[PDB]
Figure (cartoon, one colour):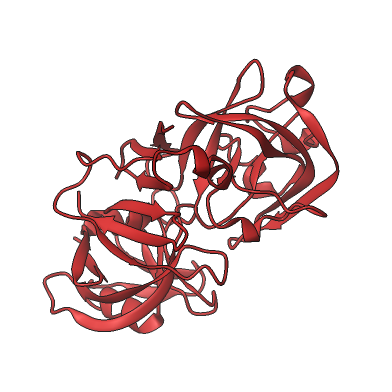
Length: 330
C-alpha cells in the first residue's frame, strides 16, 4: 500500500503545516500537524475542556462505530516549545492520503495548553518519530507509521514541505519526480527516539564550506533551524544590523535586509536554504525589526533541523530495520 497527502502552511510565515487525516467511521477529518520530532497522535475532541477549545475541529469518538476506549490508558506530553496536552486513549481507524491503519491509538485530549487553544488551525498532532517516545501509559502505543510499515510497498515516508506553498507527505514510496539530482542517504541514531543524524558542515551565502560535524534531528514539528551558537553567529554576522535580542528571545535583523543563503552538508552533498526562507517577519505588527529563522540551540541540548531546513529539501525517512535519512535538492 501507499498514501499521499498534501500538507499546507497554517499561515503566511510557514509557522507549521497541517495535513488532513480521516479518523473513525464515518470519517471525521481533522487537520493534524505531522511531527517527526514526537510520537503521539493526539486530537482535540469532545472530551477536551470546553474553555480550551477555540475554533478547532474535534474528534467525537461516540460518533465513530469503530472507536473503542483503550481501557486504563492515559497520555501526557510536554513539547520543546513549552506547550503540553494530556488525556485518554481510543483505538480507531485512521487514514492518511488513502493509506488506512486499523486499531491506531488516537489520543483524545482532555486538556491542552494555551498555545494549542490559541491556534485554531491545528486540530492535533500526528507523531512520526520512533515509537519509543510515545507517552501512553501503562501500555506504550505505536505511531501511525510504525503500524502501517509492514503493509507499505517500501518502509519509508517522505516530507516535501513548501516555502509559502503546499507540499506533500508520501507513505510507502519515493516520488522520483519530486526532486532534482540524487538522494544522499546518511546514518541515523535512534538512541534518543529521534531521526538523529550528523550534518557534515555549513556555508554562509557564497562563503567557503566549513567541514564540521553537527549532530541534530530532522523535525518537521519545529519551525526554525537551531544550530550551535558559533554557526549562528557566523551567519548573522553577514547581515548588517543583525543582533541577538534577549528581550525578543533570539536573533533579529532589520526588515530592510537581504538575507544570505545558508548551506548544510549531507555527506558530500549540499542543501541550500535560500535567504528568504530565513525571514520570519516583523517581531510585532508594524515593526521594522524582523525575526530570524536560524537561531542558537544553546541550552536546548540538541540541534534541530526544523522546517526552515527541511523545506529546502526532499526528505526520505527510511524506516528499514536500520533506519536512515535521505536528502535531495528540489
